[PDB]
Image (cartoon, coloured by chain):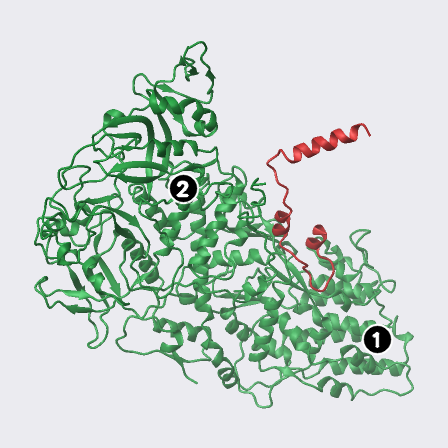
Amino acid sequence: EFISSWQNHPIVQVSADVENKKTAQLLHADTPRLVTWDAGLCTSFKIVPIVPAQVPQDVLAYTFFTSSYAIQSPFPEAAVSRIVVHTRWASNVDFDRDSSVIMAPPTENNIHLFKQLLNTETLSVRGANPLMFRANVLHMLLEFVLDNLYLNRHTGFSQDHTPFTEGANLRSLPGPDAEKWYSIMYPTRMGTPNVSKICNFVASCVRNRVGRFDRAQMMNGAMSEWVDVFETSDALTVSIRGRWMARLARMNINPTEIEWALTECAQGYVTVTSPYAPSVNRLMPYRISNAERQISQIIRIMNIGNNATVIQPVLQDISVLLQRISPLQIDPTIISNTMSTVSESTTQTLSPASSILGKLRPSNSDFSSFRVALAGWLYNGVVTTVIDDSSYPKDGGSVTSLENLWDFFILALALPLTTDPCAPVKAFMTLANMMVGFETIPMDNQIYTQSRRASAFSTPHTWPRCFMNIQLISPIDAPILRQWAEIIHRYWPNPSQIRYGAPNVFGSANLFTPPEVLLLPIDHQPANVTTPTLDFTNELTNWRARVCELMKNLVDNQRYQPGWTQSLVSSMRGTLDKLKLIKSMTPMYLQQLAPVELAVIAPMLPFPPFQVPYVRLDRDRVPTMVGVTRQSRDTITQPALSLSTTNTTVGVPLALDARAITVALLSGKYPPDLVTNVWYADAIYPMYADTEVFSNLQRDMITCEAVQTLVTLVAQISETQYPVDRYLDWIPSLRASAATAATFAEWVNTSMKTAFDLSDMLLEPLLSGDPRMTQLAIQYQQYNGRTFNIIPEMPGSVIADCVQLTAEVFNHEYNLFGIARGDIIIGRVQSTHLWSPLAPPPDLVFDRDTPGVHIFGRDCRISFGMNGAAPMIRDETGLMVPFEGNWIFPLALWQMNTRYFNQQFDAWIKTGELRIRIEMGAYPYMLHYYDPRQYANAWNLTSAWLEEITPTSIPSVPFMVPISSDHDISSAPAVQYIISTEYNDRSLFCTNSSSPQTIAGPDKHIPVERYNILTNPDAPPTQIQLPEVVDLYNVVTRYAYETPPITAVVMGVP
Amino acid sequence: TVIQPVLQDISVLLQRISPLQIDPTIISNTMSTVSESTTQTLSPASSILG
């Protein structure tokens, strides 16, 4: 029943997204589209006709005008012409950034541009909410900048064959119908037969500044490296592209340092070559500062925060790569062969060999879990590999059981390879549990007694006193267990370090450790031969030997031995002896080769290593918390102060299988004839033909760029802690809340993703939380309380700077963007004069300090007239006044009482002597031209505008401006109601451009300062007049650099 | 029985006069979890959501 319901499921949007695919993002990220080439004109401003020229006419014969001879003109030949922004209206690009900003001529409505952001509540299609004008303008400027990120392309030239120029070189545009461009690029090339405006302007210009200006021809017979040309353009886009190219050039590298980096990162196992001769200036933008890498690393950490499903596939990928590169493979039969030789009697009820072989079951697939355990060493910051619960004995076990003895053996060998700091305590408590009743020790309290599950001891606070202080364990009452504790303290592996990477190209994303440094939980000792042979001088070999000796002492104890038959004792000790001297090559591999492989692999990871120091037994330095922050508290501004109380803990444990790791430790063999320097040279060679790392570097650059853009943009509509300029305060804006900021940030993120062609997700972790106080930091804390924090000092950002530059320019050229500044005055003006309403005569306007005015505020209230008395309204001073004179309203005051005010004031405004000034700040505007010789009344337009005002939306202000003429005309009355407050008519370009002069109506010659290079013989060619006046004819640098793939220039030696 | 309608009606009136909107997707996005801890059942993030 035309109630306009069921129009609400419209534009109201959706933001909630299910994001289980963090793994896909982490394993591979889309590369930004950095380099793009533009072959067209580096301009974004278009001159358009508005009113066709008065041709033919009864005054001048048609033979005078230039158009009658079909001569192309650099400028429109029209009665009225104006300037309109139209990004890339002449460009010819290869990749589209799909962020165009286009308006229509002011005679055509342009309201839809300013209602694009937050007018989801606006009903009318012709209206928009003034309070989001600032946000809409900021979005428009951001898209304006983004659409212009292109590199100018060098096309080609041709010498002139006509006397119009002194043999200049003219650049040829690509694409079809290139004829029209030659008349637009070079205004000075036109002939000057007439006295008209265009001909006069051209004749008053310099003649040698046209076409090609300078070039750098390096190689005879190849493309010129770059050129400089005089051609139509705008200073703003030229500056933007210049700084963009400057950033790209700062990011450049050359092949020689590339081969140096690749040689370094491969540890000398791979040799690559680069050419040595005059090149052609390729462009390979891959070098970025360490700060950007740290920012990207922190963002990446915050994604995988406290989630295991996101990190586990990374570990499997690393395991697969390691298995692909490593020379170590499982010996199928070593354990069975060595255990089949022990001697035993067939009359025994038990057989140690049976039990051990039953527990081992070497399924050959155990090296996968061994490899993931190895990979865990690189990410102890977020992932803490631990032994699964199921590996421990079910009820706690007992030393009298053979099965429990073998379980203890498996756990004892498996534990030292995990990244869990609390591992040694669990190793000790594993035996302590089995030894209960048999042999006792003092524990801390009644909860964590000697009979707790060994896996329960997980934090430094639970470390038993007796374990840290050996003397508490009685050498008489507990010999075996004291011996075990001494073994743990004296023979646990010592962590070490190793250098890796190529910092001068790849940078370094290390946070809590020095660059190039990679920590290990095992001491590394480089091998000095390339033909390895079996050796027993290893940490892990000593560990296994000590464990076997401890078991042997346990069996032979006189308090425990008499429970066993002598034959069983002999078999057991023989089995332990066999296990002691097994010929497993894995400890050698871990001590000598594995660190080299990790160092080789690490720089090529998609997720660079993130480590915290390994502490052997210093309970004071065990890390207990790793946190990141993305916000700041209420009043705290300095990140070093709010970091402690605004961080979110990050980390997650991962479970492994002790059986598998023990099998790996026991059954490793090398290929029958191994020569390491050949094996690795053969294996590593393919894997350094991968260019994913450089792509990751570019992605990292864009991440920080976007973060800085977000903070700078948000610092405009709200209040933040960072210093920032402010040029758009005069544009009205609402009192922003958290929700408004979140919506604005979502829009910014969408725009940036679209512009650079990113299909994955960007900035999302920052969207959660309030974006008005963003800050990036990270810290971790030891057990003793000493804390360490890292605050990456934010680098620059070209896009934010360019956006601010365009905003600063907008503070002067707001007319060109279809925006009028100031206020409006509503009042009847009837006369035959021809002044433009956009440039009203000074006497018609008034302001707050004009004598005899009335200012009105929040207390609008009206007393109706009675018995002929005039109605009255209350001034802000408490005076009662009639409906006449000059008033001043804040606009919201009219918005909140539209209907009442219309009904009360329209008659007096139309016919009486009432004039009102509405305070707007800024507003879109519309033009309606009219014939001066005909009667014209503008009351209908103003009436519609007034009546369509809504407490949420207003429509574009309509103006009625006369049409300029180039010959004598009659006059006719005109009734005007709306005039602007100050000058707002900077958009106009020329009037009667094809005629000798303008007789009636507003007059305007070609803006001379827009062509300062041509008009001023003394100006240097490279002068610009920003931010006050944008020029329309500049010196443009066009490049011809190559962007070859990495493998095309650097080829390895097989 | 006398009290019940009064409180119910005032609750409804407050519910559809206030600008506040209750949106649990805030909680869901902040936790940003489906089911962590692939193998071991204990996962506090899933537990609190449940």
When asked about the image quadrant of residue A330, the answer is: bottom right
Residue at 38% in and 64% down: A95
**The hue in which chain A appears in the rendered picture of the protein:** green
Q: Nearer the viewer, residue A803 or A681?
A: A803
N-terminal-most mark, 2 or 1: 1
Q: Position of residue A272 (x, y in %)?
A: 40, 79
- The vertical placement of A463 against A1004, above or below, is below
Q: Position of residue A359 (x, y in %)?
A: 79, 77
Q: To which chain does the residue with label 2 belong?
A: A
Q: To which chain does the residue with label 1 belong?
A: A
When asked about the image quadrant of residue A420, the answer is: bottom right
On the image, numbered disc 1 is attached to which residue? Answer: A556
Q: Check disc 1 and report its element: helix, strand or loop.
A: helix
- Packing grade of label 2 (10 A; few <14, some 14-19, many >=20) is few
On the image, numbered disc 2 is attached to which residue? Answer: A723
Residue B22 is left or right of residue A771, and the answer is: right
**The hue in which chain B appears in the rendered picture of the protein:** red
Q: Is residue A184 visible?
A: yes
Residue at 56% in and 55% down: A302
Q: Is residue A798 visible?
A: no
Q: Nearer the viewer, mark 2 or mark 1?
A: 2
Q: Residue furthest top?
A: A867
Q: Position of residue A514 (x, y in %)?
A: 49, 61
When asked about the image quadrant of residue B5, the answer is: top right
Q: In which quadrant will I find the C terminus of chain A?
A: bottom left
Amino acid type at circle 1 is: Asp
Residue A309 is left or right of residue A31, and the answer is: right
Q: Nearer the viewer, residue A105 or A215?
A: A105
- The vertical placement of A837 against A670, above or below, is above
